[PDB]
Image: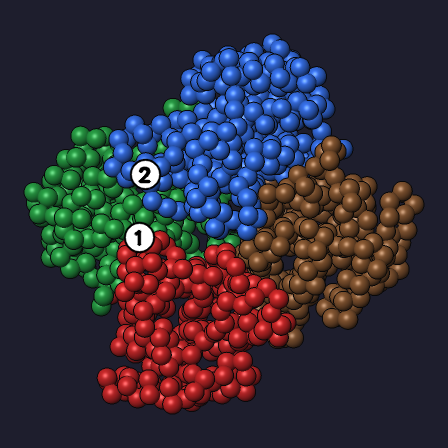
Chain colours: A brown, B red, C blue, D green
Amino acid sequence: SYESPFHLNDAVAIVTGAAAGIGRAIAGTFAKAGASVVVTDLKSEGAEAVAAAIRQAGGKAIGLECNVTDEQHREAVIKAALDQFGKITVLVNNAGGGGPKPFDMPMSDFEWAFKLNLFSLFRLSQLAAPHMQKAGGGAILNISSMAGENTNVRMASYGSSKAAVNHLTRNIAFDVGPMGIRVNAIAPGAIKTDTPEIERAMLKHTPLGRLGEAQDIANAALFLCSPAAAWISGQVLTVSGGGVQE
Amino acid sequence: SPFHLNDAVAIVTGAAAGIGRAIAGTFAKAGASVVVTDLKSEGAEAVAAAIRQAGGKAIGLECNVTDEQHREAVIKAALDQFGKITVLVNNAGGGGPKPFDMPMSDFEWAFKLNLFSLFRLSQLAAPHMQKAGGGAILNISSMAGENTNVRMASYGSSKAAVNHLTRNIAFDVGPMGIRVNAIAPGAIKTPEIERAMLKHTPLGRLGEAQDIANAALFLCSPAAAWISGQVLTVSGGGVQE
Amino acid sequence: SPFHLNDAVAIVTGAAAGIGRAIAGTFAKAGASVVVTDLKSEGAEAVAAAIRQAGGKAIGLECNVTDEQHREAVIKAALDQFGKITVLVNNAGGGGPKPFDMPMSDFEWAFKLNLFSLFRLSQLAAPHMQKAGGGAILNISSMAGENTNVRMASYGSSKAAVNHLTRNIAFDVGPMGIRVNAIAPGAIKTDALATVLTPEIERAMLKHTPLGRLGEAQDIANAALFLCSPAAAWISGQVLTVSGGGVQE
Amino acid sequence: SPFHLNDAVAIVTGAAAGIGRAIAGTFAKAGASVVVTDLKSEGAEAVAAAIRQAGGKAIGLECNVTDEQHREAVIKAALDQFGKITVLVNNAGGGGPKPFDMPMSDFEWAFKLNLFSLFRLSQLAAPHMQKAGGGAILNISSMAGENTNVRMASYGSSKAAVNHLTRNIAFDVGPMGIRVNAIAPGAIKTDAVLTPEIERAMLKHTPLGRLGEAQDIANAALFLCSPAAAWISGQVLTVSGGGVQE
């Protein structure tokens, strides 16, 4: 090849929770860099909308419903990718959720964070790995959170499931490296998405003095899933303007 | 000397043998009354008996820490017997090397046993520690929570979640006067292969269970009163592999 | 796309060979006018000439980064050549394994060359980058700044100082519009190493490298291009480890 | 207890006041013959005299830790007075917030004082520790070694160097019978100027709701230099009430 290694020409990319925000920028970006994209979401309307806009833009995409915590949903996506495009070379695990919860929280909540943030993406990684190997190499990207490394009040379930996403990333890179597969994570800072007094106090400890755009994350994501990052694996890259947003 | 647990009540889980037993023994001799727990209660009872024989206050219970009934029984049984809970040592856990393509039940059990169990106990134990004007939680983690290897997907990531849970709940239970810390212990002896195990261990010897109990005592004592949210690696300066 | 250095002026230090040289060539390809620097001026001149012949803009200059007059000379010369400074890559550095009982001068020298030099050049470059409305500084650190081992008192601690300096001065120069990041390369098969490297040493180095290869100079240059481009407009204070997933011990 | 310094000879630098003084007094009480060091000799001997009264053994010497002739004189004074060296607490240090554009002399000085000095004294002590069949080195670092703020170029980066040096020389000196550890103290309420709303601010992210005491650190120092930590080496122990004091 003679194109820059910053493209995904030939690639096939599953992006989860991609109807809005970071996930949506990743889907559009991966497509414009030459990937055929499988957009998934909890609501298929949002997923299909994203896929259609990609198709409109010149790229190749399909849009699907996926509850990443549902086994038959996870397997359906894997099947749909191969049926449509014939291989899987990139997995972006962007689906997740949760937030401040009190210490005394119900035990169904604590277990939910791990079900949602961890178990889903680990399983999705097991499912994709065999196919990426057959394709002769892949990249997995986990969208984690800065809470995975920060410490604060009300963060028992969210902070600890994210810290777990970080370390699974660092360890499975050992498992799947010999299969040709790289595994990294991005910890995004606060993303300005859909009150200019609260903004000045969100950015009190942010050196670059602005909120993120979803496109900042997607740029970092494209680098990390591209051949320009071919020798990078097991890494957690924090994209937050140099500090913490609160 | 603030390195003594005089007037203290400590639950110590998975404490039949190994690290948990040496911590149960040591805290007892440190001045504390000990609710020893274990999967198999003949293991638990034996340790409790040997403490009483040595001249200390203790009781031994069966507890499968992944059982909400077993968990609450331990709390009640601590309270009936000794009148309060002041120290909780989460030593029960398990797992190890497992292939990347393990069954999901294997993966989930790692979290159930190593993480879910100890987070509940902490919740259960906490209000009583507050009611006692303060306390200390101590989690026995693993170096796998910090290190990176092959076959470590479930065991490494769950021990990593335990470390960061420790750092974060220190913020929640801090205002309740509770301190939360963890220990990551190296390879514990509890001749040819031993030289090779020691290849990246600067102190040139394998661990003793007591080494861990010594650090456990410091952290759970008033001499570490302004220590919270920490993960202390006790491994002679390196990794045993 | 956002991966180009259109209109940029980059100083790349210690850049006659290896990682420095791949960064200089790649930044020039990406659109930057490049001031290639090296202890040996003929070496820097050679890379600048290749950049020029490949259809790019570059000069090569002598520079001992530990010499205050060389540093300021370099800064003035980049401004005399191209009118502004928007990118600084602090690739010059050195040192390695040293006994615990090493003379103090060995220990201090690791800081002088690895840390004091790149701190001073960042100071000198910063007000120029602010006048040009934006900058990126990139420090080439090392995995030794994170790992622990025998014979690393001066090399490891000096590189850990680089990593943390990077995290901290990000706070200082972010309000000037400057981003500061570092790369910590693992073992990179340059022609310095590839000559010395035996197949059986290489195998020991691959033992704990999940990707099954040593790195190439271009791996580092690609990472460096990302980190100094618009594609990383919102990344500062980071240390990106490029190590193929593990360690090369 | 295993938390005693019986038969120990401990050198403690910067010990006229604050943390250094408390470590010295505490080490004496735990059985150590203490060599008390300070920039001002009258301060060093004041701590030494006080110790001698309360029932321990301590000499007081003047020492600028950045001066080789001084460093060597403490070493010799300890051997002459007590016959051996088994423990070294490198507590002497300094610096703090500095502007980015600081003169190089200031940047370089943070290293001469916080790092070059403790490394040299470790070099000097180590042979006498080996000849005595073991010892412990304790570096007093700072939370600046790990945290990130404005104005921390010289101070933060020198303390990070201290931390990583501790991790690394643990390897060089462990086969000599020597452990090397560090303490990163938070804000410690020594005799040091602090107002009510300043202190309230520092407590905002301290979970335990109090600043620390010199004795908090001394206790941790005692643990780390005692046989109860005989298998602990290369560690950085943060004593900070569970959070940060900023």
Give residue B163's position: percent from left, percent from top: 49, 62
Residue at the extreme top of the image, as rendered:
C80
Badge 1 vs badge 2, beta-carbon distance below 8 Å: no
- Give the crowd class for mark 2: few <14, some 14-19, many >=20 residues within 10 Å: many
Give residue D98's position: percent from left, percent from top: 45, 31
Q: How many marks?
A: 2
Determine the residue positioned at 85% across, 57% down.
A84
C-alpha distance separating marks 1 and 2: 27 Å
Element marked by disc 2 = loop
Give residue A99's position: percent from left, percent from top: 66, 61
* Location of residue B40 (image quadrant): bottom left
- Three-letter amino acid code at the position of disc 2: Gly
Q: Chain of mark 1?
A: B
Determine the residue positioned at 64% across, 52% down.
A181
* Same chain check for tags 1 and 2: no
Numbered circle sitting on residue D93: 2
Classify C136 as above or below B223: above
For this view, does A188 lie left or right of residue B88? right
Residue at image mark 1: B202
Residue C115 visible to the viewer: no
